Length: 341
Ligand SMILES: CCc1ccc(C(=O)NCc2cnn(C)c2)s1
Ligand code: NI
Image 1 (cartoon, rainbow, N blue to C red):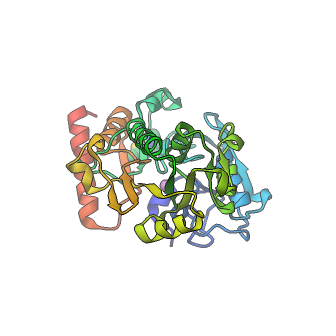
Image 2: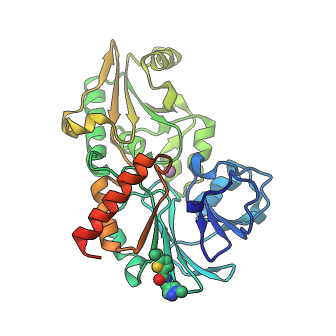
Image 3: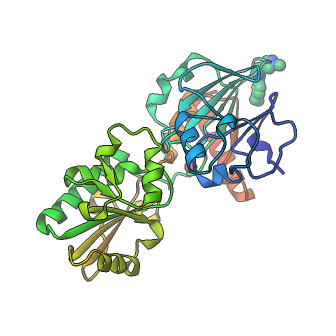
């Protein structure tokens, strides 16, 4: 059963609704981005039209093996007609190929679905500035004031400086970065750049990165592990056991590992500043957890919503508990009363 918050009223459209079988009345299935909770249910045997970005479409074709005839890529920032309804895709500032969708209903209603997003003031000068939005389907992942984290720029600065210092002190140190999905590519690309190395990785991850339209990508990544001093591994292997085991496989080339685990928010953020972050260490292995977020902080979310002034908000995350729903509704009312809409 498809839940109400994945349906677009007055249309034959659903958003990120691939795990409910054939949805009654659905003429087009939109996919905001290539993350498993959102594409859950898509496969090579899917036979309905899928609307998405060019990058998302590359991944559907190459990773999930969806047939080309059912993939409908749309350009960003461009008015398009889909089954008689005007739509626009906007960059979501999430992972590569992630979009927000503007729907212009035949009756005059305007709906924005953010997908997953990290709100930014640059969105206030997109095609959103042009008109009123009546309903907002909002990524509420971190909709509570305790959720603070630094900018992506500050986090990258910390990681670059940390890696460069360690490897300059010890040329036989290896840097390892964890991953379990697309997104957060800047972490490992920025580190490899400062160290004058390509990033080494599995054939499967290399394949995924080749779908993302990153400029000069052939210059930045490789499957030849031996030529590389920045390696990518599955997030599950970023622990003392997993990393000891990996060091053994490198054949006495290295005698130290420095590893990074990009997480979302962690309770550590309430106490410590990014400058003061320290690793967990065991012998010749150190592990840094760094708060690189691709979702809005509470303050970023509040600013976007108070700017947009929607008439109704429909949360799409943390909808499963009454306590969550009650908390989110209280903040929406606070924001409205403070700003005056
Ligand atoms: C509470 C959230 C809303 C959903 C749609 C709204 C709206 O007013 N749309 C324009 C419009 C005017 N007349 N008709 C029929 C639609 S308000
Ligand atoms: Ni996501």
